[PDB]
Image 1 (cartoon, chains in turn yellow, orange):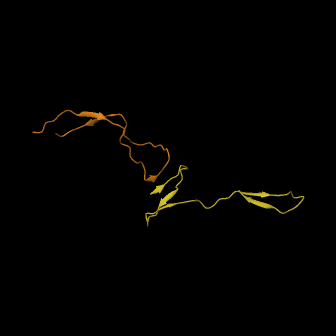
Image 2: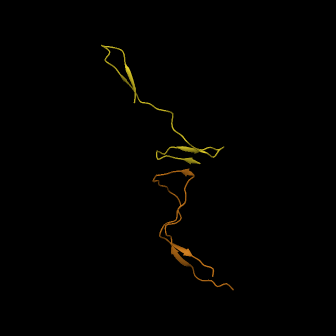
Image 3: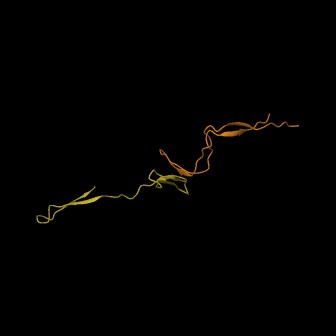
Length: 50
Length: 49
């Protein structure tokens, strides 16, 4: 009825209506960072998603 | 009129493993605790001849 990954987590599931196996992937997660020239110089900044 | 004869014996050659759960697992090594048949154990044999 279920699958589980080696991270102990429920990776996949059987649909009760269609008995079709479905794989889950979490909502996208992102690492965020900010770059600056130094406040005593300029305020334009660039952003980086890791 | 049947004849009866003392029990015979044989050996548990690594059988009696059964799925412990209804969960799909793959490419993995996993461990459990339950009732299972001990390997290499003296086990009884009967016949009807």
